[PDB]
Image (cartoon, rainbow over all chains, first blue to last red; front, side, top):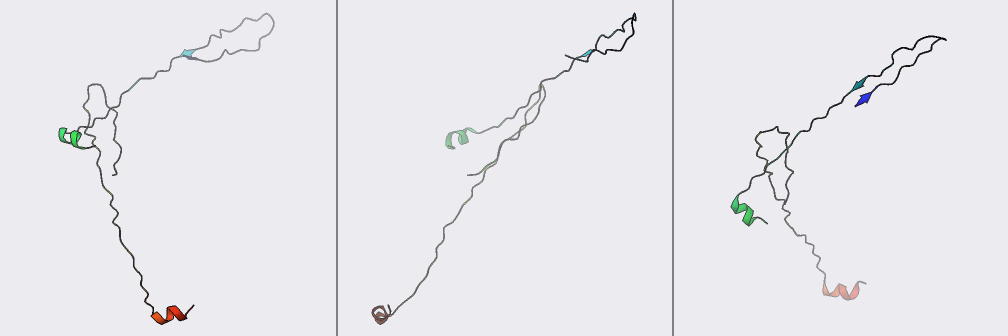
Amino acid sequence: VSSAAVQWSWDAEFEEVSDDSPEFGQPEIPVKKAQGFVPISIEALQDEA
Amino acid sequence: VSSAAVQWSWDAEFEEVSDDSPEFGQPEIPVKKAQGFVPISIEALQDEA
C-alpha cells in the first residue's frame, strides 16, 4: 500500500477547513517460473565420470 | 575438457521444456622439440681458454 501526503492550506480566522483526506494505491507483483531440462542416456550416465 | 552453460527459459504453467543439452570439446596441445649442435676439435679444448 502507498499513499500521498495531506495537503494543508493557509486559512483566515473563523474559516472552515477543506477536506484533506489522502488517497491510497496498491502496487502488485506476480510470481513467475523458469525451468530447464537436460536428458541423458543410460550408457553415458554409467560410463562418463 | 571444455563445455558451456545450460540455457534456461521462462516457461508458463503447463508448458513443455526444451532440450538444453550442452556440447563439449577437447583442446589438445602436441609437444615438439628443438635442437642445436656445435662440434669442436680436440686441440682447441686444450688451447682456447
